[PDB]
Image: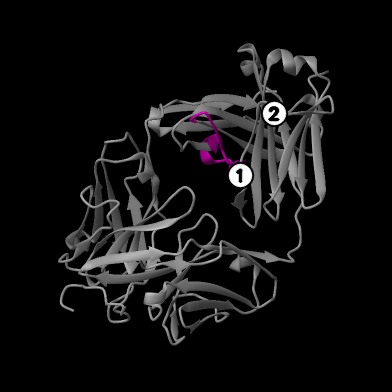
Amino acid sequence: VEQHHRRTDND
Amino acid sequence: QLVLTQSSSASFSLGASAKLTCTLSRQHSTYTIEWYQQQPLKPPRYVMELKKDGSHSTGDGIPDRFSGSSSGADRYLSISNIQPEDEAIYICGVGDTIKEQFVYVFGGGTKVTVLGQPKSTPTLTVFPPSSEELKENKATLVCLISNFSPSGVTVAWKANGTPITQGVDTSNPTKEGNKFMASSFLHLTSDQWRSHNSFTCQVTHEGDTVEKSLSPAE
Amino acid sequence: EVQVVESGGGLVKPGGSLKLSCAASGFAFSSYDMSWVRQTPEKRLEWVAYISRGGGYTYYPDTVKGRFTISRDNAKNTLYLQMSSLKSEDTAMYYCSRHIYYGSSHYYAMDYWGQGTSVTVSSAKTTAPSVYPLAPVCGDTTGSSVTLGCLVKGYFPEPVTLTWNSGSLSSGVHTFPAVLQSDLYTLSSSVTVTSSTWPSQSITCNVAHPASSTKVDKKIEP
């Protein structure tokens, strides 16, 4: 499995 | 699932080079993780973020003594020249977003002890029951245990020199400045307090014993 | 400097609800994503809510989903956690934590944490302490110093606040960890003073217990 970035507004 | 595994405890000699291991679940063996340090009576403090290749970025005010590396699913925190202030719980943490659900997992934490420090022996303060409490036909004897290091103590009470089992409540030790403190209470009837020649609070700490006694007399 | 200050913790009964706030200062709050993390009395940390810098993303783990709501007011630099349908196992220290600036890492690190606010969900009964003055046995009044104390017996919940001479006597004061027996806490504080000052001067402990709205001042008499 590959780690995803966290989501934030305007990314 | 996403799992972080770490030993629950480690000890190292003052001045030594220490290394802690955090291990990722196999299917997440390439993840970027973080290390946190929690010292007694404080919140967790960010130590560093650590990548699968061993590169890392340390948080504000973290000594140059802390560094990170990696090996497959293992993530290491290394501390050169371990100091007494490195005594703490170390916890690793790891995040992901899976199917648009954010998840964040903490390790169980590794409680770290720095051996080889100079000892401090407990000081005892013992109080008799107040006359106000005695009027209610009750007696709580109080033993206040301070200025000791390391934090493990065992507390026992005696009446006329003989051990007491019942009515004892002894706290966990709590950090106070650079030492520890604890308290113990012996609950009796007023008749019990009045009828013995002495009571003794006795504390065992690292091979030493400290006793302090008091008497209902005079 | 960077500050995040949590407030709002207290005792609540099961099924009850509570709202926590976190006031941030010393950094540009509306640039940062924020979380609440809790820590059990056995010291295990658990992430319980996330909110992005502009409020478009909020997430919760299954253990609180549907009961907890995270929100923020950027105009006031404040983060909130509304908790409802509280359970005994929600008892924990609650920390507000800042995620590392997204330009520094797009991952997960929590780079600053507040001191925490304590939450207790319990049906145990609220009980004001009995406060007894502790003067030494006569045998222990012959030193160059003398140690007096204060016994704070049988209360719930934590905390109590204890001072000596209303806070004016601060040096040589030690307040010891409470024991817990049958849903009631007991603790003691002591003050050490040179033996010339007591009992020629007055020494009183001040014990407040907010949860029962009580306060007791006990003068230590020989």
Give the magenta part as a residue range: C163-183
The picture places residue C85, in percent across and down from the top left corner, at 25, 40
Query: To which residue does mark 2 refer?
Result: C199
Instruction: Give the color scheme: rainbow, by chain, secondary structure or one colour.
Output: one colour
Let me know if residue B208 is in the magenta part.
no
Asked where in the image residue B60 lies, by quadrant, the reply is bottom left
Q: Give me the residue at 51% from left, 62% from top.
A: B109
Q: Residue at x 35, y 45 (%)?
A: C90
* Residue C33, horizontal then vertical, whole percent: 26, 68
Nearest the viewer among C196 and B206 is B206
* Chain under numbered label 2: C
Left or right: C207 in relation to C25: right
Q: Is C182 part of what is drawn in magenta? A: yes
Give neighbour class at mark 2: few <14, some 14-19, many 20+ (Cα, 10 Å).
Answer: few
Judged by depth in the image, the label closer to the viewer, 2 or 1, is 1
What type is the residue that disc 2 sits on? Pro
SS type, badge 2: loop
The answer to which quarter of the image holds residue B203 is: top right
Disc 2 to disc 1, C-alpha distance:
33 Å
Amino acid carrying mark 1 in the image: Asn
The circle on residue B172 is 1
Q: Nearer the viewer, residue C138 or C114?
A: C114
Q: Is residue B218 above or below residue C36?
A: above
Image quadrant in which the N terminus of chain C is located: bottom left
The answer to whether marks 2 and 1 mark residues whose Cβ atoms lie closer than 8 Å is no
Residue C82 visible (yes or no): yes
Quadrant assignment for the C terminus of chain C: top right
Report x, y in % for residue B108: 48, 61
- Chain ID, mark 1: B
> What residue is at 44 percent from the left and 32 percent from the top?
C209
- Name the foreground residue: C180 vs C176: C180
- The image quarter containing residue C145 is top right
